[PDB]
Length: 93
Image 1 (cartoon, one colour):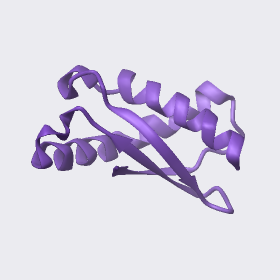
Image 2 (cartoon, helix red, strand yellow):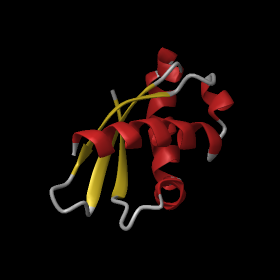
Image 3 (cartoon, one colour):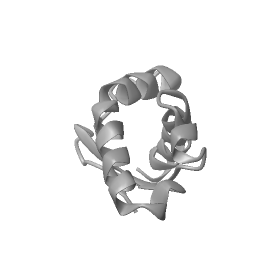
């Protein structure tokens, strides 16, 4: 799904700024891509940081973002009026 992956990159990048304080990460955490399941039960999200100045802070940043993943899924479905939204898993790129 090439077009849904482009809409998800854009809206998830905004929800990453709104649903958690991205100023705590320097207000420049960006989405580089998504990777989606054939059955849409799951998706992987790839993220690139200005908080990249510390490897231990990026590890903690992904850990804090994964704890918020259920809000991010619920909001992504609301922003798209989507019939099903995938369950979300986050990665540093």
